[PDB]
Length: 282
Length: 280
Ligand code: NA
Ligand code: NA
Image (cartoon, rainbow over all chains, first blue to last red; front, side):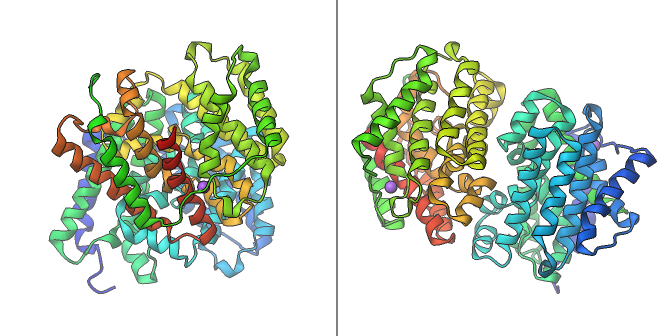
């Protein structure tokens, strides 16, 4: 990767992200703890869904995927643990699908597994909303592989890039499968209009992109907001990073105008995602 | 702000918007012609949908609303005229609902009517996608009236304002009811991810906001991007307006990376909306 690396800024940016969250969010993420029985159930369902694909995945690997759900949901407000388990399974199986060679992507085998998961854990209406979101995300992933549109949106400006990431980073899917956990009519509506996703996209994506940059550029991946700046130039990098923190701050201050429960969930998502992303486990 | 106006800029901004579309889109909108029978079918369904509200709407009002669909769809690519009629009806009855005293908003009576429209004109899955978009939009409006969240998103920055308008100005609804008109797999997916709405929100909202500004500020409505600048300050106004034209241009040039049918639809929507808005 040569000088296209954020390694020189890794510690300072980690410190600044945390400082920002401490100043602006205050409430520290907590990890939801599943019983051994609940985790086993989650993992069994994950294994079942990827079995048709001939994937064997260890518990260790599943638990490494699931941690983002354990850290980035909002334990204060959980009301439906069946829905919580659905989010665990769906998150994990999607990560596995995403890590597969796309030439092995058999949608005909995988999509009915997603449907079977949703029907197990959600009521009829919610199962359809979660399933459609999952189907929309994997379909978009397939459409945007080596696509000129992805190139155009990702390289034009931060505005076009984040617009693309509202779907691509997975947060619209996340919101559409997570609202049944909270049974909160306002949150449910913000999830369904995708306003929830639009509010949280930058705080999730900027953190994810920062910590994935070196790995991605080494693999020739273009979907990272830091590709819009000359990371090798400390002055240009610091300018850009400050602009991204300011974006995160503006979003967070606006999130604080939503009703209390909704803003707890949105902020626990953005902050919890950062805690997980930086964890030794991750 | 209550007595502000963009009247002094009306002619110049109209010319500039048109000049921009001529330079960046080139292909001009054309109006879909409904047969007499199709227009009567649309009007009859509109009337039926709003009848339970005790709402009496003139044919001329229906026609004034339906013109946005006739001008802003993409005639070169229309495949399914039943879907097209559904968008006519859904568009018109949502306008009428929007124009009513919200105290008269009986969702119990209105939502089953929207469901009936969707079930008449769309196949089963598309009927569900359209109805859910309609329901989300009208439920959103009800949640945001006088909400501190709307205030926050509309006054903070253009980024927050447009983010709110992806839903609030109706474009996500429009895409999710319009894809069955085209039956084009790529467009259908961009509509269902809402990328379609994200790409076209600024070009629709900046135009709608400019021409609705005087009416809206006089009614204390805060959902207008021009309230983010002092329209009484000519230099400030020109700077702001140029920034919004630059936003529209950037979205349009990015839209041209999409597949040809999809870009045709997106650009016909933004440019058609401008043509209808200026004639209505
Ligand atoms: Na948390
Ligand atoms: Na047109």
